[PDB]
Image (tube, rainbow over all chains, first blue to last red; front, side, top):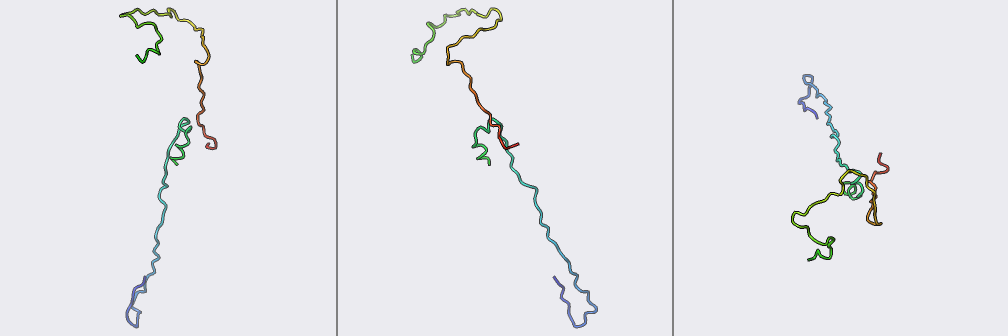
Length: 52
Length: 52
């Protein structure tokens, strides 16, 4: 973005400073789900299938 | 009355009927059976393949 300046002679005027603004974009902490099945519970495959 | 076909003893105990213990001393047992009463169930726990 720029300043406007007025008149024909600008020798008294500060030129516009170019400012190279930057927008950050960042990952969150990863989101997870945890469950467990014991070696008895794993005998029924619907537990893994439905929990997945 | 519905229990009478399933009866296993000839009479109900008398009031304060005495108890006789057969194992007067500690002793090792000799075991007897007719086939089909004494059984082992066998099962397998679901230890997963491919995982770990």
